[PDB]
Amino acid sequence: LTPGQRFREAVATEHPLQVVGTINANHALLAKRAGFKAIYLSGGGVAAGSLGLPDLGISGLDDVLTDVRRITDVCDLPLLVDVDTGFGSSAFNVARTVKSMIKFGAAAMHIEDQVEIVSQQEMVDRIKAAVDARSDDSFVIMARTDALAVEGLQAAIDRACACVEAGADMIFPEAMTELAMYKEFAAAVKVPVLANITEFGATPLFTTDELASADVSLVLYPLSAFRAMNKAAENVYTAIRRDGTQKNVIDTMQTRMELYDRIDYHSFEQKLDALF
Amino acid sequence: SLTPGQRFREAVATEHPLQVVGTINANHALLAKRAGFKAIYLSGGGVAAGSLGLPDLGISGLDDVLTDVRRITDVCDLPLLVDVDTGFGSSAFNVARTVKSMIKFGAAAMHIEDQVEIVSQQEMVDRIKAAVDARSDDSFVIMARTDALAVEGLQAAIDRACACVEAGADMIFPEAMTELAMYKEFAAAVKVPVLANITEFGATPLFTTDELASADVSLVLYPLSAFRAMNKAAENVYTAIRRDGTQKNVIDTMQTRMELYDRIDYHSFEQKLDALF
Amino acid sequence: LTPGQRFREAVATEHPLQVVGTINANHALLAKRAGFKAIYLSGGGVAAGSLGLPDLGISGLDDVLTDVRRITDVCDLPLLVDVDTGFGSSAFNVARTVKSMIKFGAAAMHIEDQVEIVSQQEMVDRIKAAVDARSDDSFVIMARTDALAVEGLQAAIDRACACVEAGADMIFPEAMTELAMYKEFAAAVKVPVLANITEFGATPLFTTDELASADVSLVLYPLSAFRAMNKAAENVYTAIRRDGTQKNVIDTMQTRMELYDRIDYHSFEQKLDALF
Amino acid sequence: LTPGQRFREAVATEHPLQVVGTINANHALLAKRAGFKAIYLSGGGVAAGSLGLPDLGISGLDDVLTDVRRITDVCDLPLLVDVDTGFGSSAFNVARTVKSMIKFGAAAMHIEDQVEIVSQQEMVDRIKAAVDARSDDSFVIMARTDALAVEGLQAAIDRACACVEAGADMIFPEAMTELAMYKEFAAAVKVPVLANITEFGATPLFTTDELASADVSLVLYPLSAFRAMNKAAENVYTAIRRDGTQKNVIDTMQTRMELYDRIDYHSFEQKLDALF
Ligand SMILES: [Mg+2]
Ligand SMILES: [Mg+2]
Ligand SMILES: [Mg+2]
Ligand SMILES: [Mg+2]
């Protein structure tokens, strides 16, 4: 099965499909162990986590591809990738982004209508460029739109429907904060709709049962694990500096035995003995 | 201003012992700097297990490590000590490429070890000579890591360590040293700064900076401590989301958006544009 | 079709199949236009051409994979890649080499018995490692042996046969100076044999006709294009420094117009009209 | 000496300083052997040589940095690098480009006012962002303008003068074709002026004496060696396909002995015997 096929199979069998952000290869394997069928490479995560930069379009295609290759070399879960507006203003840049994502093992990408937004025609054209570039048609192109906050609900639908006619497989509407609005949007666009349930934003923490009731097909948790990981790391750094030892934070740590199980350390001995 | 190696030497000169914390990525390098550490570390076990999701069995290569060196040192000015395993290839040419690359990508220090079981004292000394000869900035620190204590005993470790120092090694990292009296004897004999590796769940006890200072240890390394806690916290988030169909029961464990914006200096970007424009 | 299927297809339908060294993406397009069915990434070429270094094992997996991705992103000819001894002494290292070459678009690789050579079992163990790692069985694993130089022709046949047993798809014996030796080697091993025909070596400059009558399946020209490129470049630099102008060497230059045709500049314009 | 100090020194001791295109690390060493004091990484050559792509802004920062690192790892001549418009539209992208070029060991970069061209103030903003990001003031920021061809000679001089006020160290006027105009321009802008003497374009093949008389401080041969290298390689591919052997083109090849001398093969044994 190709990555795109695994992504489409996951959307078809989980309602809605939980897609969890994985900041690195290690966390991709934790997400797999936890039972998730699909994982996410957050652009904000590549910026804030891998580069220690804010999410202001400083991160480019090479930075993201490094994290895509690391993740997909060890974890076979389908990876949805944030590619912002396509890493360059030209149809040729969007095309290079698509071909690179497919070669480095991504399952899907979302591309957004950020330049305020571009015209329905100009968003339609980024999608057409992406669909044309695609060498494996199972690879999923998800249109991300911030049209609800700028033009109103019907404009959001119109634009999403134009992206679908352009060959977008799924829709990611931004800044949508009522279940009743998701249900109307989902009926009007037809294709799978993703609900972005991040923390500390305008959206309520909608449950999978609530989103299922509103006919939402995907639920994304873009940075959740990253946020808990940073609080836990800061706690260790504070304690080592304050106490001159890690004695008082040992109880917060993954054990060496747990780490050896999560990266399948003993499968490597078991491979040596099978071959030789 | 100072070179990375100069900052590493100044840190060792002004902190007794110098706490050096593992930073799995650029974000955690900034957290360590905020916590007040003067030096940071790029664990090769952490590049393998964290960046690659692989065991620490020499699968990870120079290019995996250099990616993480460049990410960290592009945004964090703290001196970065880098695990380079045995130099990423058996040849003096391979050791030289590693050294010139670490320096070009902005590393302050590397440790290179005598693992294969250890190689002969002569082969370890040759590794150190190749590293020293390749060094283009003399301030860059070459730290010799030896497992000679476990394989051949204390006196053999001392002799191997002194031969590495005669070969130009700036600092020594003895592995498997489990008693304070052994640190004190070793430090008195080798003369150059000694690093104590205080990792968790191993045979080494969790010695405090006070204890290590009394044993005349110059550096204490906490190589995967933050990473270990990061992984348990991420696993607890994944488990809760899967079970509950929401992250409701793990919101309390999370760094806030406002906290994150503060730790990556989000508002310095607005203020840079104000200054230019 | 997969790159490996395309490479086996080429061996099967050209006798012997000519495989030319392509030092960069530009020269891979020139080789495709010149009508070749297969191309080659020389490890000596990555070293001397991409890194400006001697072929002394300084170049490693990431140097080669950069050149693989550059070539395979724009040229669809099956690419045979020189991977030395596997870029690390462990079966884990050989596994990561195989999996990365498949991922980054390579069609085949050769792996050799250099340490003087390793024992037959130690060479069998590399091949079993590579074969076990192969995600796509169409991907070609070519065993390269220097056993004829060290242990005589009967050893060379024996080692080759033991590599074929281990799942090596094709054999690359090193430096045969007589067609009779090649004819015997081909008949003993059964699987396709590769004749390395480099310049300024001990080997004669055998023709496709000669090697076809010795039952040789591939013929490699590893650095031919590169050696002519370097003399031409050196001639340009010498003239510019001597003359204070390039006037007297413009006659040896590919024109702008030819370059534009060789990198299909105008097809990028014909994509802008067909898409928008 | 830092790389930027080496470029600055070369400009003050050669009138005009010849700067030649080097497509790869091998050709940077050929340039050094030729006695050039400075070398150039063409953006068009990264695209056409390294990627086999047209020069339409498909190439990005990571493609360029790979070649910068390869060249500056073996060759100590100051490298001038083409960074297009800075690889992203924001001050932060330009700042990342500058810091990367300095870290990977580039001596200088040229950044251009292309979009048609941006406003004088938008170009000044690019230069201020690059100057502000510079950690090593010895690193040379050269402003490239196509103002002459859009707005005329006085416009181009005013723009070049505003870029100098913003900390631009040198100026690269595009599509300038009369020595008289070079001479006027050089007198007006005061800082060193580069003349781009590429083949098969509008500009005459002006000599170093001719450019010196016009008070031009640098002359660039951006792709000269690469054009010769492509024609040479193609001739090898055609001859191998037709003849079924490279025998009839051996005389156009750098010999093995010459290759080993140009990559200093024997300095590696001599390094070994000195060390151990
Ligand atoms: Mg994003
Ligand atoms: Mg280690
Ligand atoms: Mg080779
Ligand atoms: Mg250019």
Image: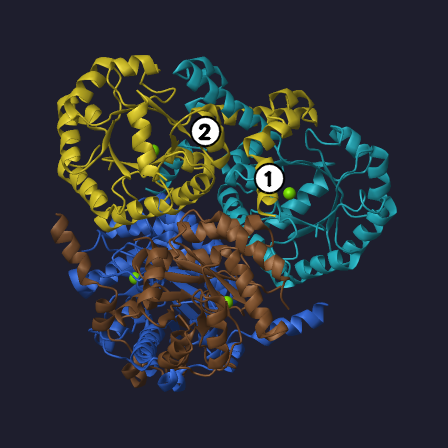
Chain colours: A cyan, B yellow, C blue, D brown
Asked if marks 1 and 2 touch (Cβ < 8 Å), the reply is no
- Quarter in which the N terminus of chain B is drawn: top left
| Horizontal relation, residue A208 to residue C18: left or right | right
| Horizontal relation, residue A52 to residue B248: left or right | left
What number is the disc on residue A126?
none
| Horizontal relation, residue D259 to residue C256: left or right | left
Between the residue at mark 1 and the residue at mark 2, the CA separation in whole angstroms equals: 21 Å
Q: Chain of mark 1?
A: B
Q: Residue at x 54, y 51 (%)?
A: D129
What number is the disc on residue B271?
1
Which sits earlier in the primary sequence, circle 1 or circle 2? 2
Mark 2 within 8 Å of ligand 2, using the beta carbon: no
Say which residue label 2 marks. Answer: B33
Relative height, residue D122 to residue A170 (above, below): below
In the picture, residue B103 is in which quadrant? top left
Residue B209 visible to the viewer: yes
The x and y percentages for residue D243 are 36, 85
Q: Residue at x 53, y 65 (%)?
A: D160
The crowding category of the residue bearing disc 1, from other C-alpha atoms within 10 Å (few below 14, some 14 to 19, many at least 20), is few
Q: Amino acid at mark 2?
A: Lys
Q: How many marks?
A: 2
Q: Residue at x 45, y 73 (%)?
A: D195
Q: Amino acid at mark 1?
A: Gln
Relative height, residue C150 to residue C13 (above, below): above
Establish whether labels 1 and 2 are both on one chain: yes
In the image, D32 versus C270, the foreground residue is: D32
Residue C191 visible to the viewer: no
The x and y percentages for residue D22 are 38, 68
Relative height, residue B233 to residue A155 (above, below): above
In the picture, residue B205 is in which quadrant? top left
Q: Secondary structure at mark 2?
A: helix
